[PDB]
Image (tube, grey):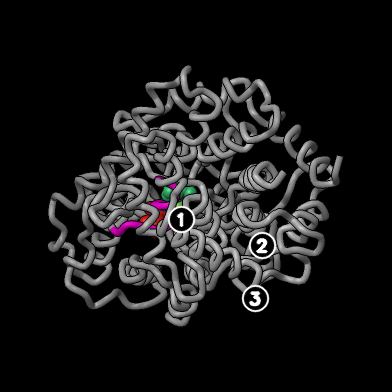
Amino acid sequence: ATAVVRCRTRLARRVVAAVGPDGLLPAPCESRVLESALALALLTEERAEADATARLTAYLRTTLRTAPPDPFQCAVARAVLGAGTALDAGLDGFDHFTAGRKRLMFRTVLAALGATGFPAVPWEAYDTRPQQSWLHMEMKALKVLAAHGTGHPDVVRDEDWRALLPALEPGPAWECNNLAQLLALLALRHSPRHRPALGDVLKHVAGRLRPDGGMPFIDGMTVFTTAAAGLALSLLPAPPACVTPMADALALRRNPDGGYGFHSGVAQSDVEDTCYVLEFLRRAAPDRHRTAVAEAEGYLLALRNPDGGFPTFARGTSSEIAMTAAAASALAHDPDRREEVDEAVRYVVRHQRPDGTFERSWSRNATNAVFRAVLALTGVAAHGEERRSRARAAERALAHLAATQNGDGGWGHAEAEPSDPISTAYAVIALARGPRARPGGPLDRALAYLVERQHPDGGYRSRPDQAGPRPLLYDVPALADVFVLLALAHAT
Ligand SMILES: CC(C)=CCC/C(C)=C/CC/C(C)=C(\F)COP(=O)(O)OP(=O)(O)O
Ligand SMILES: [Mg+2]
Ligand SMILES: [Mg+2]
């Protein structure tokens, strides 16, 4: 068969072999400068864990020497190893509804580490609506830090301290979020009422160091990765048998609200994880997991905003394009919810930008939202005026992909970035919904790119695309193989 099919096959054997007997594809997260710096600062002011703080220091210097991250994280590392131009630079026109909260978050962090002055804002600026559980704790921690850092500790209300109590529980980070626990602990250490519980958690934070001496942003993304892998495998001509244990492992980890978190032990459900599990289960076990499917469908239908879109975590927060398209695709299978599906799709078409693109949210490349939108625009059957409206929106999106394709056949994070396999995989999934591949065509060139970039061990090593907190990148290496396999499975 073709070189693409041969590439697909080798990659699928690799992905299958990585699924564990428990039905999960391990997806650990790499060390990140930001959390290693916060961990270095915490352990250093508490004068604890000399061994671990020595490693964290060597990791920070080496990473800055050999693999510098964005200017914000560099300023954070430089601030702890020892800058307002770094905020302007890290958020270079960060186009997103969170930009205001982020400018506050990131400046308060830098100030907490002694790199700049705290923001001259009313204390209410740190007040955030109920959303993901970790955001509320993070804003409360930064409010505390700002109150002690500026010399006004009497400003801290007892409802602020209360929000940090999960950080003092033993074991792994609450919600698997290291940044959130490290921020809470940096605030908690200023409270004598809470220092008794602090020694125990410093020993478990210190034991989280990865072999390279760094601290990961999160524990991992095994649910997100397993679901994505299972969905890719179930789109092969003949799916491997292991999709059944994978589906079982996902379904038994669902949260009380019927949604799914990104990792084992994450109580916060989100729309992105839920849609991948739902799409996957509907193909590999619609009957064996009928109930899980129906509960996940009910979860999404409860998050839905009145404007037709879907948020990531909690209704009432801004709808997002990628999430709205993802939900429309996952909800389309049942004809009971065609009203909600069409309204979601219409939301997608209204927010398409004049150049045919959509948004940069949880992925730092434009192709991610393009591929979500194109699937919804072309997967949800329509007729008459609507079919023509959606086909036009899909054409403009695929055309934007063709306009920005690089000579080597791939796409980068942005139009003038060098190609990377993940950004290209997203593009391929979308292009696979356009016209059939012709020689020299955009999709044809994209497949060849993926073929050439395959590693002798059958896998892919790609620049990461995941953001969190946005726009900060974090690296889950296992996602590369999965998303490329997802692309090759749609395209072949
Ligand atoms: C799983 C995917 C790909 C989509 C849904 C969102 C999730 C679970 C992302 C990955 C896991 C975490 C903790 C974040 F990136 C979230 O980080 P934050 O809540 O600090 O991000 P801001 O809201 O501050 O931008
Ligand atoms: Mg955040
Ligand atoms: Mg976070």
Q: Earlier along the polypeptide chain: callout 2 or callout 1?
A: 2
Q: Please report the residue visible at 51 percent of the width from the left and 40 percent of the height from the top.
A: 224
Tell me, yes or no, whether the highlighted magenta stretch contains residue 324. yes
Q: Which residues are magenta?
A: 318-327
Q: Residue furthest bottom?
A: 85
The label shown at residue 416 is 3
Marks 3 and 1: which is nearer the front? 1
Q: Please report the residue visible at 40 percent of the width from the left and 28 percent of the height from the top.
A: 293
Q: Please report the residue visible at 20 percent of the width from the left and 49 percent of the height from the top.
A: 161
Res. 311 visible in picture: no
Secondary structure at badge 2 equals: helix
Residue placed under numbered mark 2 in the picture = 62
Q: Residue furthest front?
A: 384
Res. 63 visible in picture: yes
Residue placed under numbered mark 1 in the picture = 387
Q: Spatial distance from mark 3 to mark 1, Cα to Cα?
A: 33 Å
What is the crowding at mark 3: few (fewer than 14 residues within 10 Å), some, or many (at least 20)?
few
Estimate the x, y position of residue 46 in percent, counting from the top left. Answer: 39, 52
Amino acid on which the number 2 mark rests in the picture = Thr
Amino acid on which the number 3 mark rests in the picture = Ala
Q: Earlier along the polypeptide chain: callout 3 or callout 1?
A: 1
Label 3 CB sits under 8 Å from any ligand 1 atom: no
Is 238 located above or below residue 68 in the figure? above
Estimate the x, y position of residue 274 in percent, counting from the top left. Answer: 42, 38
